[PDB]
Image 1 (cartoon, rainbow, N blue to C red):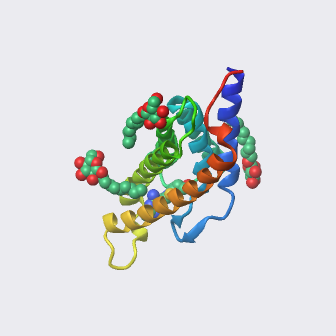
Image 2: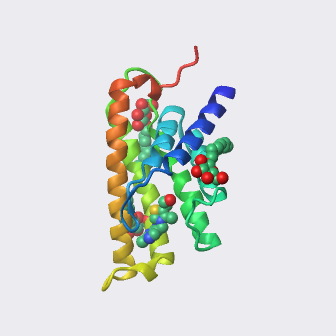
Length: 176
Ligand SMILES: CCCCCCCCCO[C@@H]1O[C@H](CO)[C@@H](O)[C@H](O)[C@H]1O
Ligand SMILES: CCCCCCCCCO[C@@H]1O[C@H](CO)[C@@H](O)[C@H](O)[C@H]1O
Ligand SMILES: CCCCCCCCCO[C@H]1O[C@@H](CO)[C@H](O)[C@@H](O)[C@@H]1O
Ligand SMILES: Cc1ncc(C[n+]2csc(CCO)c2C)c(N)n1
């Protein structure tokens, strides 16, 4: 009870602190390293924990003034649904030894793809006034959010491979 809750809370606060690190490549093409703590949380504690972690992270972003909000529905999509959706990594939780790297990677792939799918949808609806010269709404959003999603996946792969090799205990919960 108290262990699980403190972990959800610490991973959400860490996601938020990490989102203060400058992460822009160009305009909205970004490297979203703040996903990582929520991915770690979901992989270790499962679907529900991760969902709740992402929800808390999203709320922190909004209530501290760090979220970019264009409307109620845009905020719902990009700062509730999108961060929550990272919890899908938890379907790839490993409960028993030995820890394999592949599930970690697949979970991450799927979770980051899902998050950036929601950003892609939002890009079409809410951000198309910024589209580059000659680019339609769909094309612009696919580029921006596709690229960000790939870069974010990259960063998550690199960090999580390091954690697997150097801190494998992180990925498997044990009582005792
Ligand atoms: C549910 C658990 C919640 C724990 C979250 C506590 C950590 C959040 C602190 O954020 C701070 O917000 C300030 C706004 O006043 C910013 O100026 C500052 O840069 C930033 O560091
Ligand atoms: C692509 C989005 C939806 C796909 C969700 C399907 C995931 C199936 C997860 O079951 C698997 O069960 C094993 C035994 O428990 C785990 O050890 C393993 O790591 C886990 O991967
Ligand atoms: C991080 C990169 C973001 C991924 C963007 C890829 C979008 C691919 C959409 O998947 C799809 O699902 C089915 C129902 O949703 C649709 O019938 C199908 O036509 C659609 O293409
Ligand atoms: C084309 C386009 N431009 C901006 C955004 C907005 N956006 C992208 S990632 C993100 C969350 C990072 O905190 C937000 C709000 C978008 N979806 N698509």
